[PDB]
Length: 379
RNA sequence: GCAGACUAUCUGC
Ligand code: B12
Ligand code: SF4
Ligand code: SF4
Image (cartoon, rainbow, N blue to C red):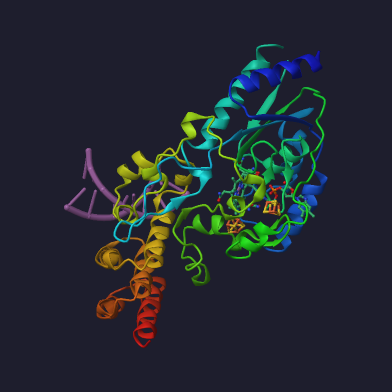
């Protein structure tokens, strides 16, 4: 009966393109609770987590008289067909794989809405669904439901699809039989830990999110200097601890057409981003997950990417931004970039902007830019 | 009306 409904749910889930489905109880996540507290006391959380720990670990608080949680996963593509080439004059930035195609929040919610209506259409079933923006830890739910195991890079990693999956889940009042957690396949490997550009993976399965490039790309303020050279040409997110992972070798699934990257926005030219209108940003980037904080972090990161490529051809546009952009973070990061690119011809204009800039943080960035030129010109 | 900022409000033309 419940066994029967489970069988049907699984069947239906697959038919609407869910790539993996699991079941667990609505029992409290005791281990997670301790973990969240530890991470918090260490200053290792990101701040994107639901702040109420009671709600994060207690399904029955979220859904009264809850009995189970249904976990779903969808595999997303890891290779971009016909990626454009980033040339000396036409430099590009890159969005992480989790921001290719239609925002996964929309895709996975659509599927959960269907799973919910499936159950409602039967019987007194009650549900509460979430993807990423709900109170639960999606990874904790998926681990306990047998979707994948918790690898050393913190990713839920599946045998079929690797770590390249979007997670979502649905709390119900249906006493489904739970599944069994699956085996840890990392063994003695430490490739992700050694590859991480900032050492954010401080121990296996432990992230200092404050040092993680994926977090850093999404911040709205000034990027701390020690990361300005580690971010490379990343505009949003970071994939290094997954792409380097042996468990992901060969894993390039194209099962969902709306997840297919549009190469011109997944790997966009940097210079046009510096001047994009809001209307144009909304039209081009508005349906990818990477636009959820608007265009400012993206534009800040594109400035850093151009400094990274030392693109002297961006120096006039950067000079205009340093002067004209209404945002202190953009004027300041542009001034730093001008100094970083290392064309002594712009030293004078930095000196002149310093005397005109009123914002103290931006003034400081112009001073750093001036300093960068002074040091590099004397080499 | 347009453009911008901030995450409805604010600011210009
Ligand atoms: C905040 C946030 C982040 C933060 C912090 C990530 C992190 N590792 O904590 C930042 C902004 C850095 C980030 C980055 C990314 N994230 Co993110 N993020 C989230 C969010 C909203 C909550 C994460 C969270 O609560 N972390 C806190 C830690 C403490 O818990 P947890 O990871 O959720 O759960 C595990 C640990 O607690 C661990 N644990 C528990 N007890 C113990 C005990 C011991 C001893 C140990 C060692 C471990 C351990 O086991 C749990 C289950 O795996 C979730 C969505 C959600 N609501 O859950 C997405 C989510 C984790 N992110 C996701 C993605 C795709 C990413 C990126 C790959 C995006 C990118 N390409 O840049 C990177 C990967 C970074 C990484 N190596 O982990 C997916 C992961 C899917 C998957 N297959 O695992 C999620 C689930 C979103 C989704 N629904 O698809 N993210
Ligand atoms: S996402 Fe990038 S910065 Fe963050 S842990 Fe993985 S490799 Fe390190
Ligand atoms: S790189 Fe190695 S240790 Fe890290 S998640 Fe992959 S298999 Fe596990």
